[PDB]
Structures are given as structure tokens and as C-alpha cells.
Image (cartoon, rainbow, N blue to C red; front, top):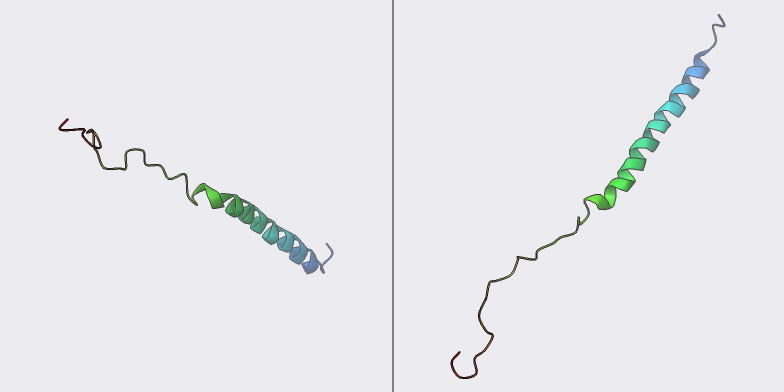
Length: 59
């Protein structure tokens, strides 16, 4: 039976509590960058203009 066994509960809960933190921290660190500026693209993000920049005389 061994009545005095409350110290094992503290050591087992302690490691289990910290271990959870490592899993959350591990994903939290990698999580950064995935959303931090995904890539930012805008090929069709400019004004349209299918005309010559300048003309020689008229055209």
C-alpha cells in the first residue's frame, strides 16, 4: 500500500505539465513565418494601358 506517496504525484504531474508546454511552444515557434508575410503577390495590381507611351507624330 505505502501510504506516503504524494511526492510521486508532484514529480509525475510536473513533467507532464512541462511536456505539454514543449509541444505548444514547438508548434508556436514553427507557426511564425507561415502567416508572417505569406508571399504577397499582385501581377494584375497596376493601372491598365494598352496604348503606346508616346507618338512620333499622331499614331
